Image (cartoon, rainbow over all chains, first blue to last red; front, side, top):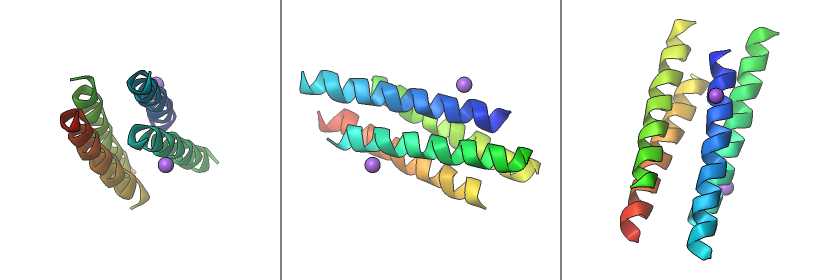
Length: 26
Length: 26
Length: 24
Length: 24
Ligand code: NA
Ligand code: NA
């Protein structure tokens, strides 16, 4: 349960960092 | 560049934690 | 900024994972 | 164990993000 929730959190952080990486490019 | 690579790393950690969460269940 | 807030998030998760390791 | 190694990974990334924040 707790590890699955933390896994989803880390996936979401990954998407947030990718969006920041993109905004920096554009 | 570096943020995109770290984003991929965090996605991969997410899959590793999800696999650990699963192994624990089964 | 925003990256610092994410960095703190990751350090919080690291503490949670260490706690889970020792829970079982 | 394995979770501790991932926790250390996350603390390493947190330091990288803090460095990127201050790079620019
Ligand atoms: Na979650
Ligand atoms: Na990578």
